[PDB]
Image: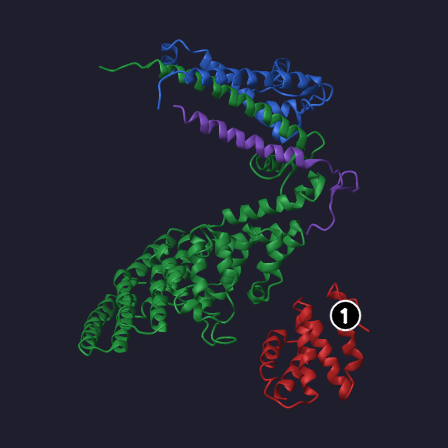
Chain colours: A green, B red, C purple, D blue
Amino acid sequence: VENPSLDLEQYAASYSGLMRIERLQFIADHCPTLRVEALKMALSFVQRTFNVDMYEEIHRKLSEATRELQNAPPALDTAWVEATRKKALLKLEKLDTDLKNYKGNSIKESIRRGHDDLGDHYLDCGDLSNALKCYSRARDYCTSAKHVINMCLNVIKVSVYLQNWSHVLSYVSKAESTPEIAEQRGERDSQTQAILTKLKCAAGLAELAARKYKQAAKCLLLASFDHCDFPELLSPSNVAIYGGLCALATFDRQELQRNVISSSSFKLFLELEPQVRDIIFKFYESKYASCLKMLDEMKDNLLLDMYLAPHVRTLYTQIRNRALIQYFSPYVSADMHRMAAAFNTTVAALEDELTQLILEGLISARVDSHSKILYARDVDQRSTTFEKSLLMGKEFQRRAKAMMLRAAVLRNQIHVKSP
Amino acid sequence: EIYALEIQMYTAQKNNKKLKALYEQSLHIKSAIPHPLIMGVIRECGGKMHLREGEFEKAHTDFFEAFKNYDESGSPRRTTCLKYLVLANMLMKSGINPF
Amino acid sequence: DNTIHGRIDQVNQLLELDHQKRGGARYTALDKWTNQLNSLNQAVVSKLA
Amino acid sequence: HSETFTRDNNMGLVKQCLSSLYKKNIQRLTKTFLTLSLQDMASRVQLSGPQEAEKYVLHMIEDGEIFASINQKDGMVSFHDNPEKYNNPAMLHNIDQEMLKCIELDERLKAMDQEITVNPQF
């Protein structure tokens, strides 16, 4: 697991919050050589945002990182670990009394202001389970629909770092149909508040992990270019990579052109990613020799990504499959040698490749391994209806034998008793 | 008339990412205004970002209105604006009825 | 995109065209009746014991 | 578990399954390949050597488990893959006979329904 062509400077640029620490740490993990770099970049931002839970984690890896780098031929700043810790520990108690003296006031908006400060500084220190609850109680101290949303957005933010995606979606489903179906029209012709652009960033990414790549594409394709850089979940440069490769695999040729290629909504995101754009195009243009050539060499980088690692087979393979169907179906008889180099492989390989797909998949075609050709195999309608009718009738006859004897055995009270 | 000169500079520059944003915003401002030649200068350049985009049904109608503004006043683009009204109807894949 | 109803024999450099049309209704319709009887008779067997 | 099987005196029948799996393996090939080599088959079925391949081809055919044939000259197996088109008396007779057995079955049920006629009330 490694790729040299990787820019960590950009990887950190578009992200923030915990997402910076989570992604930087996943890169350092699966990508060595750039573990020298990746652990230094997690360290620096952990020292901001009053964070000890992550420093004790991250810096401990820096030691074992440099330890293994001395096997080819930094120090625990405990002066700082104390400094941020007591600073943070007492800042909790300040915000504690701030909320407790906001609760003594009995103001609806002032207590929600307190709550949102508490959850923030418990997030800061790496504490998730505590940070979680602060926003939950902020539901009670509300009035408007916007207040029940502006908290429900935060509710999700944390349930992403926690990795309970089931509750990510439970509160997106609530937040979506909260203000009478998103204020009806969307704030009268183009909204300054890009809100659902976020709500579908999560509704998708939650499904991404949950294997529903088609349901994920539906939520990631609707992602408009109003929200762009939302660093605490997923960048727009990834929304293109993620939702594009998702649809590609699970979408037919028809929905592609319509809901992917010629749709302006998502078109802007494709512009951002020129390589992702070319593979979606070369699929539809049916120039497969290149289509996969591109995708293979992208696999190296896309694996090192945090959220696109765990679907790198089911997607990549499902696309290959899709194309293999789409290449052949039009032909009644196709030369395998042409199809071979077209799918970056060998003749013999192609032979077995198809074989499996014949049995399982919808490749209704046989193999002539003598001259290495693939012929389309279509059904003799007549034979079919005849064939089965005999067989079904013979099954019906067999059960009729059985339930005639079964009428007899019960009629005679036939059974082997125990005692 | 400010958005006219903005669409005129980026038509010389070839910035389709801003031009698309500019034309969409110069249709809400197209309402609260009297009536100059300029109201066709933006429509012809706006139709060009629906030929480029692909949706020829939103370029076709754009080039009919821009052609009409050069019809009333000056006609430097009227001789080449009809080229985009006809090119639309053919590529509209249905029209085939220009003149 | 499914405008031209046809398929290609790449080896022979030609195009056989969709056309071979016959009574596909009889067989497909009877197919259903055959299926319903299959599920039906077993429902009558599972009644008695 | 040679013991467990031979304990029950049904070893042999368990070894008939060993052979029916070889015959299942080849039965699948019909659905995928339509022209295949003896050597290819020998390598894919696991029997090894083109004879062992050609063997079960013959037997399965001779018996009538698979529709296939051999071109020894090249050394290839061609899968006919095609039985009957329901276009003759052959079916017509079987259609007559298989049907008469369903009517035979109705005759029994009709008598068995009349059996229930005479017994007590409700």
Q: Nearer the viewer, residue A362 or B95?
A: B95
The picture places residue A184, in percent across and down from the top left corner, at 46, 70
Chain under disc 1: B
Q: Mark 1 is on which residue type?
A: Leu
The answer to whether residue A5 is seen in the rendering is no
Picture layout, residue A48 above or below residue C27: below
Residue carrying label 1: B87
* Crowdedness near tag 1: few (<14), some (14–19) or many (≥20) residues, C-alpha within 10 Å: some
Q: Nearer the viewer, residue A17 or A379?
A: A379
The answer to whether residue A123 is seen in the rendering is yes
Which of the 4 image quadrants contains residue A66?
A: bottom left
Picture layout, residue A58 above or below residue A388: below
- Direction from residue B86 to residue A242 in the image, left or right: left
The picture places residue D66, in percent across and down from the top left corner, at 62, 20
Kindly identify the residue that appears in the image at 39 percent across and 10 percent down.
D6
The picture places residue A261, in percent across and down from the top left corner, at 61, 60
Kindly identify the residue that appears in the image at 35 percent across and 68 percent down.
A45
Farthest-out residue, right: B99
Under tag 1, what secondary structure?
A: helix
Picture layout, residue A315 above or below residue A221: above
Which of the 4 image quadrants contains residue A52?
A: bottom left
- Direction from residue B10 to residue A232 in the image, left or right: left
- Direction from residue A81 to residue A15 in the image, left or right: right
Picture layout, residue B44 above or below residue D27: below
Farthest-out residue, top: D9
Kindly identify the residue that appears in the image at 67 percent across and 51 percent down.
A286
Kindly identify the residue that appears in the image at 75 percent across and 84 percent down.
B70
Q: Nearer the viewer, residue D107 or A35?
A: D107
